[PDB]
Amino acid sequence: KIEKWTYLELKGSKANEGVPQAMTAFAEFLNRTGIPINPRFSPGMSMSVPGSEKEFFAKVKELMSSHQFVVVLLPRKDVAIYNMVKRAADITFGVHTVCCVAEKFLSTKGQLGYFANVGLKVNLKFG
Image (cartoon, rainbow, N blue to C red; front, top):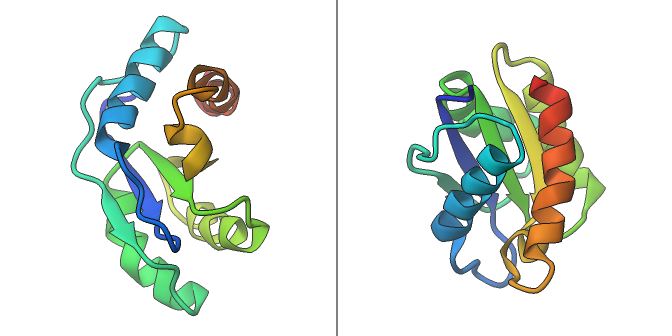
């Protein structure tokens, strides 16, 4: 059972709406599909994309070292931001991160299908 988790939101041009609410929906989804997780998350973090990996690691370091699981929302399917996230996760102990595109994670049509795909990655990390 994932007990301590939160989310990290990497800002794009447009502001994301309904994030906390979708995170709750996501946790419910995970529980229904056989991945036990506390239905409640600790308050999430939102930040613009920093200029360097060092700057990024400094910012998210406490977040990632104090949680078992972090759901990360990226503004676009940009593999460079994705890599920045994976580098920090690579040197952090006791945490798993999963990266998602914000629009897909939030948009009503196709949300459940997307949740299901993201759940594949989550399952592999814990199951």
